[PDB]
Image (cartoon, rainbow, N blue to C red; front, side, top):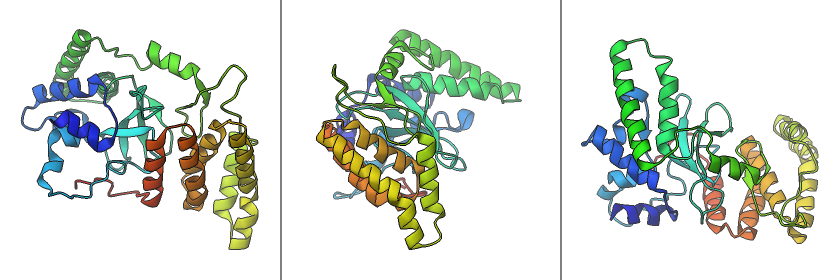
Length: 310
């Protein structure tokens, strides 16, 4: 049972559109479903789709495969689970975004990891995410034979979504309801959702604005010496004390935000403190799996060679 296998290996449930889209791709190319969109869109299905693909099967147990790292790009936060890849020149990729390991994805996000850390919303299911990508591709293609192929995939995609009841919109009602719960955008822009009660307990803002925090981070990276770097780091050390205060007052979202911003900034100079902030924040929020993902990822934060099944 590949479905049980994929959810066991990632320790995450997958939504029904994940499995329906596999079937859709099997229909497009029965022999190599994960590559059904490679020629027309330049996209390949990977990650949990590798499991559906049976790519993991040839290896003999114990393989040592770690799904926490599998197709995890450099700026993928633990919430983001890659399912589609494009060109490695930009490291374009799409992933399911989950606010909690115990909840189904709230949308499909996209990022170009060689460009920046920003995660853009691209529909709430993979049919929508591919439809929206295809629509953009339609504006760039200059060969009527290739346009014909894209129109055919578009027609099949739209009909499948209609029968299954999936919205093709970039932002759905459900996504707008989730974004109401966002307490801060973070550096990746995709939003952080943590519980906030009636008395406002659960989150507090960082004592620096995002722009000033980036200024501080840049000073750490640009520092000419260890002593210079220590002085530049001082505001971040102070913010970690403020996070300790917040944790004592149950405002666990603050440490998640600081840790996420530091991770998003991308410098290895922040891996130690990110490894203090983020596992603790996720564990306090009872999002235990995400603490394990960030521990694994910070220890092996690869720019290239993230395919555990290469």
